[PDB]
């Protein structure tokens, strides 16, 4: 029961910044060969430069396009022989009050945040089942469990991701594959930075620890779940929120 | 503190059979003017015949079509003056293991089971907010909370529905509108009633009460939530499962 | 229906607030209601309040041994087997864990948790005889989310939920359901006193933007006690205005 | 964000066998000075023998007696300077149908499984607050969350432990102390049981120990008031 990921191959979607970036760095530093994705060639290049010291690399992935995720995964499998760890972190927000919410704001969220996970998870499955080993780790927000005004779309997608994960866990468990979610609370990121103070102050006041978390806190939890230390943990949602929600 | 729905107007989607039919009958018997929907003209006619004794009616609704949900709700508002209660029960299944699930099986579930609720809930909102009164009640399987092999799609949609509901509850609560889910467990429906007896016993064994529930049990819970007896209940998931899951 | 005609109900802690509303509501629905208080004076007041519905007040100090058991035996002999038990009796003894007295821990566990063990056990034999048993435990939102200064109260209320789930699994084959109702911010005398500016901090946590009423809890209990909830067991029904959405 | 516990002092109650034993071994191997407890002298001796290679030791702790928990913790604090990690694992079962359950079966469970945690957690608190650092980790069974026939007493105690932990987490969090629970499912100590899991097998005591090490470490500094389920998918909250 070590966290040595030497010889493992990991795919981290949405690895250009914040939580995704920390996850990729952490798995790479633990010994995994890491492929991190971004939606742009500049994002991918940055990931490649950042992961270079650990032999990791950046790749372009537009989750909306058909057959792109599938090709990427096939390429990884062919080049490296297997995919051991999939971290689904790619996601966007399109916040609006339901009263004002556009159809496209709903649809884009469901496609980018939820369908993307269906596609990636399905694609890695054949290989993982054949090897009788795997980790799928989905990054889902606290908002998925408690709901949030202005985020009926984002919350629905993140909650759906949890329902998806539990169902997948039941399908693939007999082959030793675990499927879990990590639920960040208020983590210091671009999204939390753009917040006004009463909102920020209101958020920190809800936490037991009295502070925002760090992207590294999420990465730490992902490493734990990706490792042999979590081989009997599946279908779970691990909340990393400083005590803002205690289910 | 009564369950007298005299003077209330209710829309129940998917009211042709089973749970939806029982819900419509129950709200109607409690005094509500009930509009129940089906996907076909024959379904709608059958609903009309069934609800005739209570002054209810059947209408055609194909949730996949744009502007149909919206037009129906507008028509109800104009004909009957307001919409007090929305029960989102329309849903389908397209079961498969993730490893062979077709893209269309994913997409159709998300459209029919989840996007339909976005559309209907958005559409009734203007009227409910003006009235400073309302009930939205979403029927969400237990599978949404615990997951189910073969149903990554259905589970994702039903779990998403819960996240949606919690978020909506937070948006509309200041206007006195409540938004809740009812989560059926193993209920006797077309899809279960005709299962082999040995297989039925495997479901009933999981319950504390030792039996499949009845569609009427779900209807009873919906009536409670729709009434003045539940005016301080919002953002909740009421599990009606005979003890097969105790969250 | 929610017609409880012919049913016998015991409601512990029925003098005031939530418990009083529960007793009145079950009684008005047709049940023969026995409501409890810790003193004969309390019991007399309950008797006066329930008189028009044929209800009565009785004394129950949970701290005393054999009192719960004797009361239930007396009810069984005098009126008949119990159909409905509502465990509402409870106290608070708030303190920071750092300075919490042993007695503050022990008294909470005795009054709020062991009382439920004792009452639930005592009604069980008779209720198994009946067609449609109901045990309904009043827990607090604090049992599910925790609360600073209430490690004791929270532990007892959370324990009550674990107890209920386990009991539900034992007694279901006899048609008995066991459920909890979890009040959030319900207006009491002590919250009613708070400054208006202070009331706002509580209401801001709710989706509905207001405190609830004791009657809201009573309404939920009536639902669960009735034939309308025959397939609901081992559940915690949160009546909190959206302050917590599990 | 390492799992190096060098320089840390840990108290693990109920460390004689199974889960408790694995926890103590694991924290010790990670570098902590570990004190493990048992209710009997034979249990304490066995712990001492097992932890000897890591400089750990066994101590007798009868949670039912007053002032014993408190004295033990004070002794540890005086000898080692601080207590960094408390793992509350001590517990018993007294299973019976509620119909048959004796008052003593209820009372014993509440005393040994729940009050013991109140006492231990209270006792370590002053020191942890002074250090502005700590970990309290409570071992609570899946039965606390889902309930179990024959175990109204055990389930009530284990569920109560979770409520306690959440409340404590809210009180002590401003000082950087985290309070969490680990909920084991079916851990080895058959097909009808394994069929209830997604993984199709019983777990190992080491799986629980692995989760406790994670929570005890710097890798879990932003995790508090949580219940981490290690059940192979038997329950997915």
Image (cartoon, coloured by chain):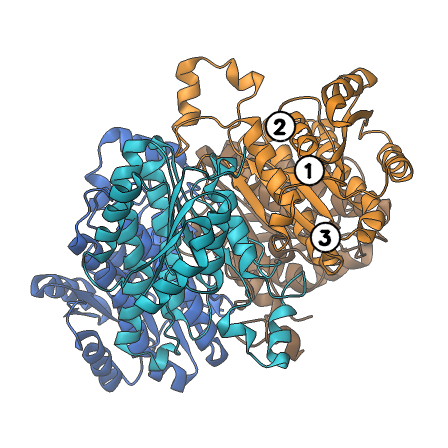
Chain colours: A blue, B cyan, C orange, D brown
Residue located 60% across and 33% down the image: C218
- Residue A92 point in image, percent of width and height: 21, 55
Q: Secondary structure at mark 2?
A: helix
Chain to which the residue tagged by mark 2 belongs:
C
Which residue in the protein does label 3 denote? Answer: C176
Say if D70 sits above or below B68 in the image: above
Label 3 vs label 2: CA separation? 23 Å
Q: Position of residue A192 (x, y in %)?
A: 24, 42
Q: Position of residue C40 (x, y in %)?
A: 83, 18
Residue under label 2: C18
Q: Number of callouts in the render?
A: 3
Vertical placement of residue A7 versus B142, above or below: below
Is the residue at mark 1 from the same chain as the one at mark 2? no
**Disc 3: CA contacts within 10 A as few (<14), some (14-19) or many (>=20):** many
The answer to whether residue C118 is left or right of residue D31 is right
**Pointer 1 indicates a residue of which chain?**
D
The reply to whether dot 3 and dot 2 touch (C-beta < 8 Å) is no
The answer as to whether the residues below labels 3 and 1 share one chain is no
Residue B220, percent from left and from top? 54, 50
Q: Chain of mark 3?
A: C
Whether the residues at callouts 1 and 2 have beta carbons within 8 Å, the answer is no
Residue B227 visible somewhere in the drawing: yes
The earlier-in-sequence mark between 3 and 2 is 2
Tag 1 residue: D119
How many neighbours does mark 2 have within 10 angstroms: few (below 14), some (14-19), or many (20 or more)? many
């Amino acid at each position: 029961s070590t966290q040595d990921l030497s010889g493992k191959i990991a795919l981290v979607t949405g690895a250009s910044r914040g939580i995704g970036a920390a996850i990729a760095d952490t798995l790479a530093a633990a010994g995994a060969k890491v492929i991190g994705t971004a939606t742009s060639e500049s994002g991918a290049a940055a990931i490649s430069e950042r992961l270079a010291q650990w032999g990791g690399e950046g790749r372009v992935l537009n989750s909306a396009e058909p057959e792109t995720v599938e090709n990427l995964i096939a390429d990884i499998e062919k080049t490296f022989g297997k995919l051991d760890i999939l971290v689904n972190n790619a996601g966007i927000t399109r916040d609006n009050l339901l009263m004002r919410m556009k159809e496209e704001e709903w649809d884009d969220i469901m496609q980018v945040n939820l369908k993307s996970v269906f596609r990636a998870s399905k694609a890695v499955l054949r290989g993982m089942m054949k090897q009788r080993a795997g980790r799928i780790i989905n990054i889902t927000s606290v908002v998925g469990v408690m709901g949030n005004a202005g985020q009926t779309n984002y919350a629905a997608a993140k909650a759906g991701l949890i329902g998806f994960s539990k169902s997948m866990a039941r399908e693939v468990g007999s082959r030793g594959i675990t499927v879990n979610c990590v639920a960040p609370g208020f983590i210091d990121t671009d999204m939390t930075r753009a917040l006004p103070e009463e909102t920020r102050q209101t958020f920190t006041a809800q936490t037991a620890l009295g502070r925002f978390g760090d992207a590294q806190d999420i990465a730490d939890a992902v490493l734990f779940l990706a490792s042999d230390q979590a081989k009997y943990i599946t279908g779970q949602t691990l909340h990393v929120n400083g005590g803002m929600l205690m289910p």
